[PDB]
Length: 148
Image (cartoon, rainbow, N blue to C red; front, side):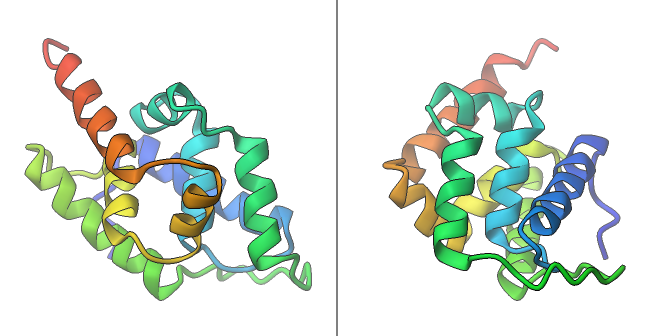
């Protein structure tokens, strides 16, 4: 029930909502989570994605190519899609596998890559990215940061 996020994971989800609204959509799917991860800018996910050349403008262009622009209709409820909810479940699994009870930005990214199917996955493929390498680089960075 969404009680297991850190502040920075909530910040990524807020940015995913804003990315939905920017294109006139009123849902958060895997692809909006991807855009929020890239654009958040400060967390582990953002700093891995940037290192790997995954650029927000490029990702936005690919997202729009696949889903287009919506009605611009805004509703206060902005629910997650089923695949996004699956990503959130997988993100909690990844957090616990890494010794955390709460989901941070890296866990959202790891969960996104594990779901592996859906608009975000297609965007990453279209950008030339390799999800297995992204995973490896996330876990590398988490380990490097252990003394803090």
